Image: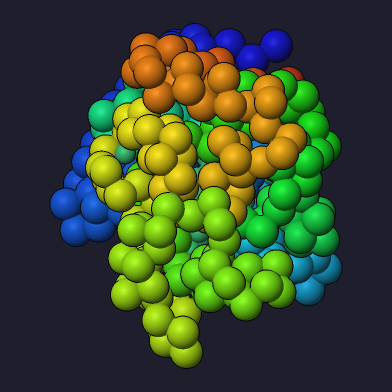
Amino acid sequence: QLTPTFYDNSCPNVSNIVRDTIVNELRSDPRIAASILRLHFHDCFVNGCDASILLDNTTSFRTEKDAFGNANSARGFPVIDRMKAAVESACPRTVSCADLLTIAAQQSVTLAGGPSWRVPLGRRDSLQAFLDLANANLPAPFFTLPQLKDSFRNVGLNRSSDLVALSGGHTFGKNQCRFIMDRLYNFSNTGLPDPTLNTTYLQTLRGLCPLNGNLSALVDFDLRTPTIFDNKYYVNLEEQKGLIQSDQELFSSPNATDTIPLVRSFANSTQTFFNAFVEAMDRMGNITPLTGTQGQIRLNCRVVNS
Ligand code: HEM
Ligand SMILES: [Ca+2]
Ligand SMILES: [Ca+2]
């Protein structure tokens, strides 16, 4: 059983050390909080939150960093190394990389203006990485709502509230032009833009992501408050201004009878969204953790102890 007080005696200042690291980093990289939250999500959706994503290549197993959903996309690894080193100095061989990343995600959300809460702790680190599983389990922006639901159910999150709330992670952060080119110029082989994309916003996005342009160019997930963690993400959806297909489908999919009321509830109330986000975050953070004597307390998050 994971518990929020797991380190209250062994490393009482772990959350503060993690917070300090993110605060400093945010001055040079305003995108780091979003990036870290995403790392935690990518950790939990592949064999659970066991820091498997933090492992680098070895001659026996490939790193998840080369997965389609991570390669040239996931970022912030050096920052995690930094806080891990700072925590190792404060409390040697005590805090697992899995827990560190979980705390880092929560602190990132809070620092960005989101809710503040104590995440359950006690997770341990994996002894291997899972590239194939990462390629199979990470959802793609072109997924239909049924596919998005299936992807979450696959890892243990059955509730549509889990999906709608966690999708709120797109209240900040960046997205490459490559992931919306179809919506802008040729959606579903129609030669036309995605009809669920607001036409005014369509023009704006086409200007940022011209056909035959730099597909790596970055666009804000939330046009209202690009770097603030709030419920504006949902207000955008109600106006057909969700950035990627998977965002807008929560409100426009023919299968959205159950997600629409959730989108509206979160758009109508910050408290309702924040409460749901915390509940969903803890549920995701509870996915198949290694505990007790299972796995290890990695000293270097990039490699298994030797
Ligand atoms: C529901 C399915 C989801 C899909 C299909 C999806 C898709 C994407 C895509 C395409 C990107 C852009 C990557 C890039 O341009 O390199 C991205 C970024 C991001 N996602 Fe999601 N995502 C999903 C769920 C989530 C969840 C559950 C969270 C966390 C609670 C999350 C948090 C983020 C954040 C914060 C970023 C920006 C990261 C940065 O700027 O470094 N995503 N997502
Ligand atoms: Ca993992
Ligand atoms: Ca926002």
Residue 26 visible in the current orientation: yes
Query: Can residue 51 be seen here?
Result: no
Residue at 68% in and 73% down: 190
Write down the quadrant of residue 209 in the picture.
Answer: bottom left
Relative side of 113 to 213, left or right: left
Give the residue furthest to the bottom: 212
Q: Residue at x 83, y 68 (%)?
A: 60
Classify residue 104 as left or right of residue 69: left
Pick the residue in front: 54 or 88.
54
Q: Work out whether 258 lies above or below 304.
A: above
The quarter of the displayed image where residue 131 is located: bottom right
Residue 19 percent across, percent down from the top left = 29, 33
Query: What x and y, as percent, mark residue 112?
Result: 28, 35
Count of marks overlaid on the render: 0
Which quarter of the rendered picture does the N terminus lie within? Answer: top right
Seen from the viewer's position, the closer of residues 131 and 16 is 131
Residue at image location 37% in from the left, 15% down from the top: 269
Q: Split into 4 quadrants, where in the image is the C terminus?
A: bottom right
The residue positioned 57% from the left and 20% from the top of the image is 261
In this view, the residue farthest toward the left is 27
Vertical relation: 189 (above or below) 25:
below
- Image color mode: rainbow
User: Residue 215 placed where, x, y %?
Assistant: 47, 79
* Quadrant containing ligand 2: top right
Q: Where 80 falls versus 294 (above or below)?
A: below
Picture coordinates of residue 108 (x, y %)? 35, 36
Side of 66 relative to 243 (left or right): right
Task: Answer left or right for 194 relative to 264.
Answer: right
- Front one among 294 and 285: 285
